[PDB]
Amino acid sequence: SNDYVNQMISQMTDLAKSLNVDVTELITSVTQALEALLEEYRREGRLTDQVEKMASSVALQLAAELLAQKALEEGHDKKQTTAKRNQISNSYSSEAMSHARAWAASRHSEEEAEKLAEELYKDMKESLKQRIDTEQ
Image 1: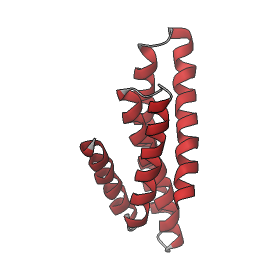
Image 2 (image 1 turned 180 degrees about the horizontal axis):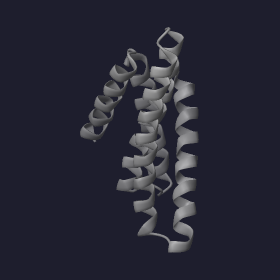
Image 3 (image 1 turned 120 degrees about the horizontal axis):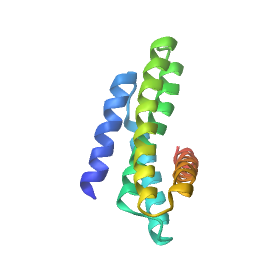
Image 4 (image 1 turned 90 degrees about the vertical axis):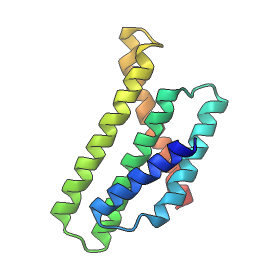
């Protein structure tokens, strides 16, 4: 929705401020990559509300890791930049996995749900990262 995209962009701008780097160039690449991933998941019948929320969390994790690299390239302090990156990335990967586990718990047996949630995160992050890099 409009609110889903705007919420993601708001959070991306927050993490950009934290890392002291301009969010501008990544907004286009991340929004386009996220849109394309969601359309693929929808077409294939893989999308649910928790999966959509998870995808925003993963996009934000990747934005933080990419923006932190640009902060290092711009000369920002390495210890502070990487500490902030790691805190932000940890927060978003934790959020993403919490959505993944909620998706899996109502749909799969207790035995396989953990592995499928882990696999969903891995596959989703790999796909988004490839899509973001293609746009960039």
